Length: 68
Length: 68
Image (cartoon, rainbow over all chains, first blue to last red; front, side, top):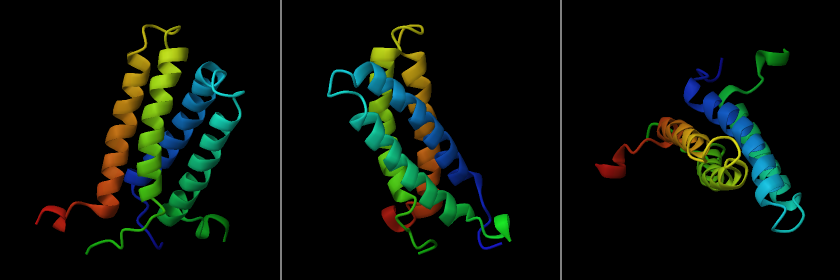
């Protein structure tokens, strides 16, 4: 039990990650087809929010005993 | 100096908030005009990630001495 695992972070990674993924595939499949093809935009966005959310979810509620 | 104010979260709230806002205004102004009008979607999304990111940014790097 390193961190108290609050809800001020889990909501950011959960809501931020999920929402992003969706709004991303949409903003790219609807507003991304104009830019280039629709993979670089939604793709780069997913990868970003992905690595970020992960690092945050760990620093907030790392899988310590999650896999003891 | 309550918290060390890391960057594992500051990146999620900063990048997540900014990106979300943009990807939202687009996914709604392009893929939202189909749903209803294009305000309920992008709007609810903005407010959501807004209050969330804020609560997180504060719980991590609250404006303690920021305005002492």
